[PDB]
Length: 74
Length: 83
Length: 66
Image (cartoon, rainbow over all chains, first blue to last red; front, side):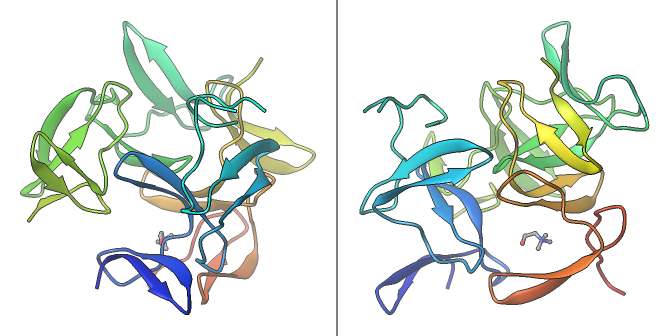
């Protein structure tokens, strides 16, 4: 199957061909970040490209809120 | 070697410049977002378009709609209209 | 301040218009490239992403069908 798939309580994103997304994924307007092993980052602040970003328990990137964050969420 | 590269805007349109001075055309993926560039290297913006039979939608930032619904049209992980 | 492809200390980076560095997979002109978390382009190596191995040549370009 395609899209979000939970395996052992862990979230992964499967593209149409079968392949696993990694990196930033946009789903329904929200941003998510995947680790290089495809697993979804959750509930924490992390650093990529020298900018700080925060994802909640659902894995969505917090944007335009509070430390501040913009449309990109930096 | 080209003195300016990547995204450049001219006449209210965005272009992508290669290090060999040529402009990129077709699909571009950068920083998690897909964009589409016409034959003359100009970026598509705020519209539906068709490539290889398949329908795609870009917003006003040229960034491709993915994993979502646009005016009731359901788009793929790679922005293709399906249902 | 400069944006676009930039070579810094022998490595290739990509800058966004807002001055930020792009990260992860890049496709342009049909070629793929992978930028590390720190924005640096992977060159001349086998690397694993999502449980799979990949190879990029000395130009940073991902090898396909070879």
